[PDB]
């Protein structure tokens, strides 16, 4: 029978009738991403006024910061945000039905000699969002931006010496919005890799150094920072885990959570357990309860185990993945908890989407999330209603898990590009060095 | 200002040739402008240019599989970082062009040959009649010992967790084009054989050469010395055996090479391979070492330990990687000491910078013609590229030194050349 299509979502259709677009790229970005976004909000039980509110802020404040509409046939900025280098991604917190999105701000100077590593554009996006949420605070943002991203003179140096960085993805920072209660919370993610190159320091040194400087004025983050650094040092110089980025909430320093992210190139349950417990340092009842759910998710998802290289820097659009990625975990430095809190990522990108959806659905049923369980797969298909669904192997980028207040928090991060009726407006998943199938 | 698609032999043969499928036609136009221009610039006579290009088109192109794109299933070869199964190389010291390829046929990657261990025999069938001096005695020995057989292939296909992401190439062929003939070589990759047999690659390679040495005892002394050197590096060594190659010719004339991957990119690591940990201290070794050091200084490889990279890259994607070194050791039948050849693995580095470094090296050896034209010719292979931003043309540079003669070869991206698209 005729199946659900996200291009039918009413808020999408109504807003399309109302909006001014002065630029073809913004119009394309809207029609490419809004069907899925509107459908995701609807299915997550956002009220109709909230659906309008969040889509309008997205169109007016965010779309103009997404750059040219991405194609393989013209130059575009390649973002670390997705494997295809596109600068936008939706995520759903399945436990509390909160929609989130992340984007990499891009403007006219991005990738030119005025801003060759895209270190300046974020300020222009912040200019547009700030008036809408008076609780936004940039104190920590400013600190990490200064310490962990390229400044103008480092940018000029690296641009003139760009053979040092070749095909490296250049993203310095992204923003994320969590959509709740007619408001939004803003977060930043900061990528110190190129700052490490220009300074001759390691990412570890930059990140731990910057947080320690912050801890002079906010001493409450020091105990978990110290524990995290001890855990890291205990793994030795041949460790499979390495620090790669930081994030923080753009809110009052009293409340903001700093997260430090470790890439974990060993894909194994043992590696994920070691991260979850920080090498047996984090052993309390609630942690061990959460660990049983990590193990259940591990068993359901069936990631391809073993050591993983870094992948190709990006995939051209239209290309079917033939790859498996490292794991990742991050650690929150809670102001009221001496032990860092882990969140782990099951990196599913490249795996069969219908099998991942089945694993998620089983997990949802086991948690008694009966709404999520019966709607998830039908809704996911509606995002890409013209696709050969059983062959897809790139919709689920990763699944994140944390356990706090004895509550499982599971989020899915999903390909968000050319959704709904876009596709109408030789089975590669099963060849190459990996097999992906139902 | 030159364009490889102007090469006369390429233009003329393009007017002459029958192609029965689009894949072969695309392979020809993709690779032949560079191939023809390379033969021209290396001073091959006109009849030689035609002879080698015709044999390539008729005997090799039909063994290259489907034309590589990102939108259709294809065999991913270990020969290049993009998984394409063809690569040209130029010996810059003697102006000899070589090409290497991985035989592929209709059964490659199917349940009949899931690791592409059988296709090579068909390619050999097409080449054998053209060159009377091809001999397969050592080939059959090494292929038996070091590549997967049908049973092992079926076992690994049903236990794919053991293979997971790994590039599956078992064996490649190489042709050296000299004096109206060609010399045929094979490279054999025992990694998956090691998985199924439980042997290390070291055990497989050294065992197989020891077995051959029963019939050819003259290879034993250099093999023993090489193994002694490897053993002296211990169990945490940054260098490990990865593959073997040999000539496909009379055993009396054939050289076996054993290849070590060296994860530590440093002049120290390079020198230790060059001297076999101080075992080679003769005048000739030291003259060669002088040039190794000069090349190291000019090329400026990024030093430090390097991980294995992604198994391959999608076509079109510029790399962000720096790679391990490699060295091989020749077992000469008339020399007790193994001879090293070292590889400066340049893939991922700025190509114009590497071409500048090679140009300086050539000038310094008095190779005036080579120095004057190297960069112009290289640009002519990819005439529409933004040359100063290229970082994937020079895969690696190899170097050996013997009989007062420095042998420098370049191995080059060979795909979508001249006026492509």
Image (cartoon, coloured by chain):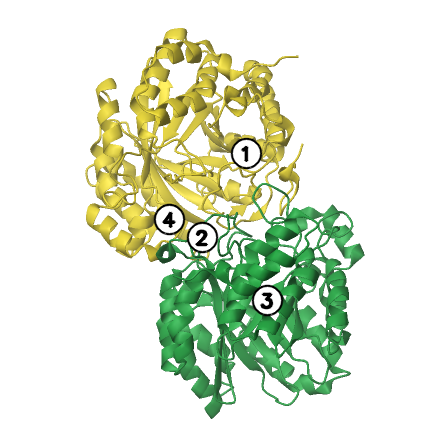
Chain colours: A yellow, B green
- Pick the residue in front: B363 or B398: B363
Task: Please tell me the numbered disc located at residue B99.
Answer: 3
Instruction: Find residue A18 and report its horizontal and vertical position in percent.
Output: 35, 10
Whole-Å distance between the Cαs marked 3 and 2?
A: 23 Å
Identity of the residue drawn at 38% across and 77% down: B361
Q: Are marks 4 and 2 on the same chain?
A: no
- Pick the residue in front: A374 or A370: A374
Q: Are marks 4 and 1 in contact (CB under 8 Å)?
A: no
Instruction: Find residue A206 and report its horizontal and vertical position in percent.
Output: 29, 49
Whole-Å distance between the Cαs marked 3 and 4?
A: 53 Å
Q: Nearer the viewer, mark 3 or mark 2?
A: 3
**Quarter of image, res A120:** top left
B44 displayed left or right of A244: right
Q: Return the disc, 3 or 2, that comes first in the chain's sequence.
A: 3
- Read off the residue under disc 2: B319
- Read off the residue under disc 4: A230
Which chain is mark 1 on?
A
Visible in this render: residue B352?
Answer: yes
Q: Are marks 3 and 1 on the same chain?
A: no
């Amino acid at each position: 029978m005729k199946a659900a299509n996200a291009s039918s979502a009413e808020a999408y259709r109504v807003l399309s009738r109302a909006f001014r677009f002065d630029n073809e790229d913004q119009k394309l970005w809207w029609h490419s991403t809004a069907p899925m976004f509107a459908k995701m909000l609807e299915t997550a039980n956002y009220t109709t006024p909230c659906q309008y509110q969040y889509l309008i802020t997205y169109k007016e404040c965010v779309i103009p910061s997404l750059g040219c509409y991405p194609t393989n046939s013209a130059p575009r900025w390649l973002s670390i945000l997705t494997r295809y280098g596109t600068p936008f991604e939706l995520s759903l917190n399945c436990s509390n039905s909160i929609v989130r999105y992340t984007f990499e701000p891009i403007n006219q100077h991005t990738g030119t000699d005025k801003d060759p590593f895209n270190t300046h554009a974020i300020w222009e996006s912040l200019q547009h969002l700030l008036p809408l949420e008076k609780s936004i605070d940039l104190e920590w943002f400013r600190h990490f931006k200064h310490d962990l991203t390229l400044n103008s003179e480092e940018s000029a140096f690296l641009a003139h010496n760009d053979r040092l960085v070749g095909g490296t993805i250049r993203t310095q920072n992204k923003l994320a919005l969590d959509l709740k209660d007619g408001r939004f919370a803003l977060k930043t993610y900061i990528y110190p890799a190129l700052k490490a190159v220009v300074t001759g320091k390691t990412i570890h040194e930059l990140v731990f150094g910057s947080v320690r400087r912050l801890a002079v004025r906010e001493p409450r983050i020091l105990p978990p920072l110290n524990m995290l650094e001890e855990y890291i040092r205990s793994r030795g110089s041949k460790s499979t885990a390495s620090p790669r980025l930081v994030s923080c909430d753009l809110t009052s320093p009293a409340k903001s959570r700093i997260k430090i992210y470790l890439l974990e190139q060993m894909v194994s349950l043992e590696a994920m357990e070691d991260l979850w417990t920080l090498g047996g340092r984090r052993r309390d009842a609630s942690t061990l309860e959460g660990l049983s759910l990590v193990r259940e998710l591990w068993d359901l998802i069936q990631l391809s185990p073993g050591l993983k290289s870094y992948p190709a820097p990006y995939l051209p659009l239209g290309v079917i993945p033939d790859e498996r990625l490292p794991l990742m975990a991050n650690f929150t430095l809670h102001q009221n908890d001496p032990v860092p809190e882990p969140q782990v990522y099951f990196t599913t990108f490249g795996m069969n989407d219908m099998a991942v959806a089945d694993a998620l659905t089983t997990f949802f049923e086991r948690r008694g999330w009966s709404e999520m369980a019966r709607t998830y797969e039908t809704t996911l298909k509606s995002y890409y209603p013209h696709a050969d669904h059983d062959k897809l192997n790139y919709l689920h980028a990763y699944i994140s898990f944390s356990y706090r207040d004895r509550t499982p928090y599971l989020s899915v991060y999903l390909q968000s590009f050319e959704t709904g009726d876009w596709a109408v407006a030789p089975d590669l998943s099963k060849t190459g060095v990996y097999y992906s199938g139902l």
